[PDB]
Image (tube, rainbow over all chains, first blue to last red; front, side, top):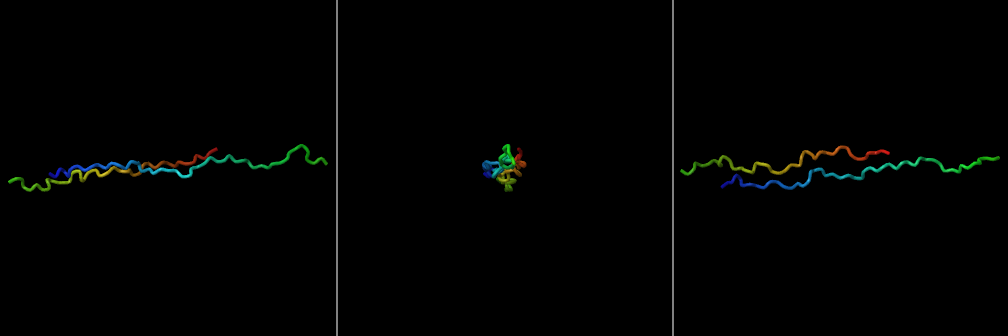
Length: 49
Length: 40
């Protein structure tokens, strides 16, 4: 007997390349800034006195 | 007369002492520095 330690099965499985990816809260496009200014009442008359 | 004590028939271990299981690689190549292409 002793069939060369009769055949044993190979190793299947491991259905994944160990990358374990996955990204958290990624970046977001900057809000094009609203240039600061000041409301006002530009008219025509400023001090007619 | 029938065979003079075969010493382990020169050796028992067949498949035992061969490939055991597929590998996982030193590391699946680590992706470079990705993320935010900040612009605009």
